[PDB]
Amino acid sequence: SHMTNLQTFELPTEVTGCAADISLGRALIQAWQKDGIFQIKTDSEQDRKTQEAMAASKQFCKEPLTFKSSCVSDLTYSGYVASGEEVTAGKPDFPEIFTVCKDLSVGDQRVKAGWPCHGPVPWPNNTYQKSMKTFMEELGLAGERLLKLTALGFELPINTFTDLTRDGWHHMRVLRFPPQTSTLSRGIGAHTDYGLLVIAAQDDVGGLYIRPPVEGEKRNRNWLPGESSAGMFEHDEPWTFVTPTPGVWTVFPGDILQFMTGGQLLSTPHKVKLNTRERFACAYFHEPNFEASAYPLFEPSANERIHYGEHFTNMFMRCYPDRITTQRINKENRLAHLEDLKKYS
Ligand SMILES: O=C(O)CCC(=O)C(=O)O
Ligand SMILES: [Mn+2]
């Protein structure tokens, strides 16, 4: 239910580094530090691609589970995940998901080489394919603007983040939540996203809650194995209902942005409440290149790094341990690539 109104920004099509760009970047940073999230206005193309992707998702989800379950690959984690498979803080989650990772044909040199997680999306139909690809291209353009403004706002060289996101490992979760069916309303537990930057779109049903930064509340560093943020604060105020709003996307930082900024930005915790109707949403992750390593921006003498490909691959093997994708990584020793990439990229 509606409480807070989020701040809304209109991004320039191109970010050049002029003083107004820097001021806008500072305002985005401040909004994340106060509210944990903000809105960015969409134009006619951004909105059209959003609506067409949501419409394709709705059509696909009405297919029988036998067909949806066939949309899997043993090369990439792209494709279908049935409801009740994903687990957050020991409890299974309710949405069914189609993950879209980088769509690489078997003729790509990385797929020929057997790099872990590299392969073609198992698209369910051509309308779904075209809708998601064009939506993700548009989302990527916004991701790059946001990353240049964020660097500028921190008085960093304009290409600090975008140097890491060339051919970035961008991917998207296409979600459908069922209607509530019992007194249980926890659609997904409280958690933080593992990536760099998150851009989210939703239908008009409502159910996403986010947690702003809280004075006096210590936050875990979810990229470290003993400091999971899963389930933390789920039942503590404050949680901000993200009111469905036509003509916007929302944006919040992930774990990698928390890591690189040394906690000046916090990975925003979020959770979803089931509603009386099914609910559709998309979460887009604007990510480093598979071969890029994140590093702390404000501690130049720190050795800590996050190699992104290793980070992603470990996360997905642990989240979907029995997927055919994980089994083929283990069978073919595809993780061996990671050590050579760290040394000879
Ligand atoms: O449903 C949303 O709006 C947020 C995306 C989500 O549920 C997730 O964290 O995977
Ligand atoms: Mn999430």
Image (cartoon, rainbow, N blue to C red):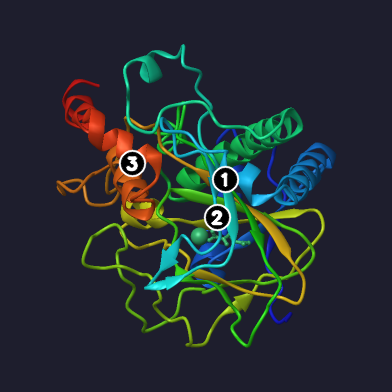
Q: Pick the quarter of the image with the N terminus.
A: bottom right
The residue labelled by disc 3 is: 326
Amino acid type indicated by mark 1: Ser
Mark sitting earlier along the chain (3/1): 1
Could you give the CA–CA distance between mark 3 and mark 1, rounded to whole angstroms?
16 Å
Which quadrant is the C terminus positioned in? top left
Q: Amino acid at mark 2?
A: Ala
Tag 2, which secondary structure?
Answer: loop
- Mark 2–mark 3 Cα distance, whole angstroms, equals 16 Å
Answer with mark 1 or mark 2, whichever residue precedes in sequence. 1
**With 40 as the anchor, is 149 left or right in this view?**
left
Task: Give the residue pinned by disc 2.
Answer: 82
The image position of residue 88, as x and y in percent, is 42, 68
Q: Earlier in the sequence, mark 2 or mark 3?
A: 2
**Vertical comparison of 15 with 343: above or below:** below
Tag 1 residue: 69
* In this rendering, the label closer to the viewer, 3 or 1: 1
Q: Give the quadrant of residue 186.
A: bottom right
